[PDB]
Length: 226
Ligand SMILES: *[C@@H]1O[C@H](CO)[C@@H](O[C@@H]2O[C@H](CO)[C@@H](O)[C@H](O)[C@H]2NC(C)=O)[C@H](O)[C@H]1NC(C)=O
Ligand SMILES: [Ca+2]
Ligand SMILES: [Ca+2]
Ligand SMILES: [Ca+2]
Image 1: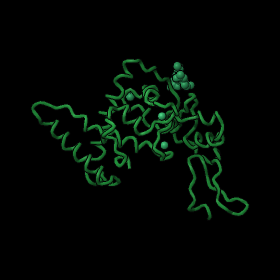
Image 2 (image 1 turned 180 degrees about the vertical axis):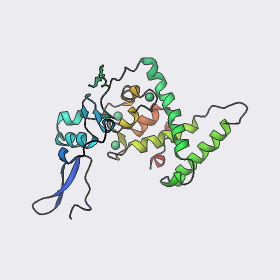
Image 3 (image 1 turned 90 degrees about the vertical axis):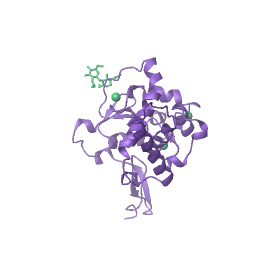
Image 4 (image 1 turned 120 degrees about the vertical axis):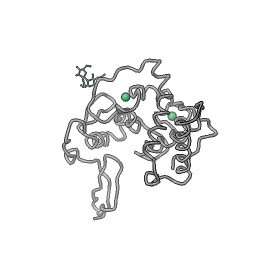
């Protein structure tokens, strides 16, 4: 009961202490379901394929406070596989291909006001504009170059990723979604983002993220990540 409304970080669970006070202990891997399929497995950064995020996160939890735990991160969903190397040319296109991908992902994702449900008004307006522009690209005699149409998609993506935990930085684990097969040149994600980790704290901060995609510091709005 004391735990029914008590929530714990990823890889943890609430258990009552001696005083009956709820407390978050690392989850029991045995209390993790068996995957329905191989696709539900995940790959850590040291090329070790855990059986599910539950298994991974619970494992990483015991290692909390440890060096090994500090460096342990989810690389990508699905079992481990051969990942080709990111050639230097690939790494140069990555930000370019990525930001267009993000814009497009945003256009088909948020198409109607029903899609724009969890978006603030400021954001709703940004996608409206994105849509106004896209329609124009589908009919203007001579297409124009529009970097502005990248600002929101780029901010959006950051907020989407900044979840575990929502702190304003993206960890190797949080970038896992960007290592999926759908992403263009996903194999360049780690190399690229490392390139973005300016102060080298192993976290990509909003300015680091934005900067890496070519968003002017003037156009870095945190509201767009709300
Ligand atoms: C990471 O682990 C996976 C699984 O152990 C490795 O993938 C296999 O790699 C060899 C060739 O590199 C193939 O014969 C297997 O069929 C592979 N396929 C996959 C889908 O697992 C992978 O090579 C490991 N290491 C690296 C650096 O990728
Ligand atoms: Ca985070
Ligand atoms: Ca791909
Ligand atoms: Ca950093």
